[PDB]
Every structure is written in structure tokens, then in C-alpha cells.
Image (cartoon, rainbow, N blue to C red):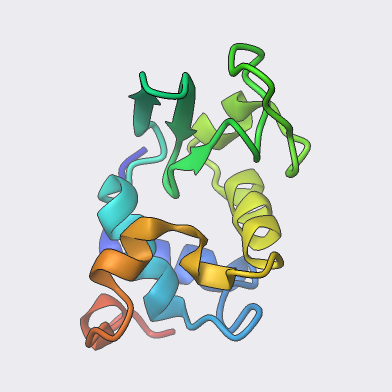
Length: 130
């Protein structure tokens, strides 16, 4: 599923993402936009370390989910990576929450640092009613 902007903003809000661990909804929207263009089916194989990034937040299989094919990987969200490819983003959100509970917080995603950190992200939630 490819979400439309405000649809996703409200979906994330209903799931408890607004201000989760101090992260605003606009920050989450900026992350999803640059990671997958709001596409729950997005996937990216990293030939270098044999890991794969899954879903709307492009969560990596080396540390966060299990796909059974990443060498020496762990599964911190304790989810099959398949759960990160569903149209319903509840599981993906639970995992994204797990990621940010760690030291780096939202900075875990290099994309957020590259295109969301110290940026004006107002536009992501404007007019969405969140």
C-alpha cells in the first residue's frame, strides 16, 4: 500500500507516534517519505552486507527483523520481516518504536539525518488535522 500524506499522518497518530520518545509526527512523516515514499512494500537489498531494508520505514534485517537469510542477524523487534510488508502498519510502527528506544533515537536512520534533521518539516503534517 502507498499512503497519501495526510492519511498516513492520521494513521501514525492513531498508533501513538505523535511525540513518541520526543519525536514529532512531522519527523516520522519526513522519515517515511524519504525512506519509502510512503510505500509499505518498499524493499532494498544491500549486497555489501547481505541485509535487506523492509517496508515504509525501511527497517534493516541485520538487527531488527528476521528474514532467515541475513548472516549473523538478530531480531530486536521480534517480527518476521514479512510483518513489515503489510498494508496495515501497526507492526511496522511497533518496530519503529523499538528502534527509537535505543541510544540514537530517530537518528538511527541515516536518511532522517540527511533530509529531516535541522530541516523545516512543517509541510508534512500541514492540513492533516493532527
